[PDB]
Image (tube, rainbow, N blue to C red; front, side, top):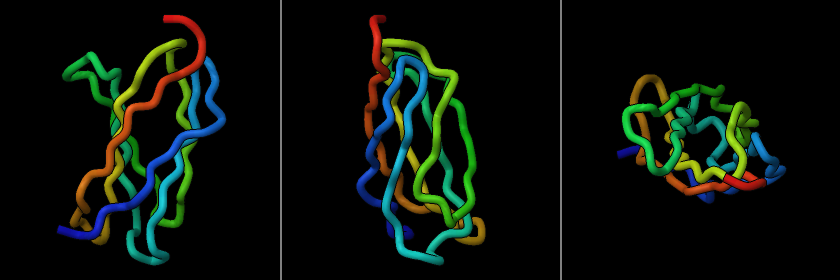
Amino acid sequence: MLPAPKNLVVSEVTEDSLRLSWTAPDAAFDSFMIQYQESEKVGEAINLTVPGSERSYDLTGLKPGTEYTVSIYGVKGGHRSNPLSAEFTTGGHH
């Protein structure tokens, strides 16, 4: 498949939000797909798209002390890359 984005990380962690960042070559993708869901849930995944020029995304509307499974894939004119996944946890108590 297409080469996946690399090194998904998190910063600016709050009780209800997270900044996601990743790496990818310039002009590789026209967009990225971002999927996230509480790690223990199924069938409740939320999907977002961002422009291919982006390397960070501010995720909001989250719950405190909650672990989220986040995956991103790169898309170039329709075809998607391998997924890149991580488990990030918000601050506070569950």
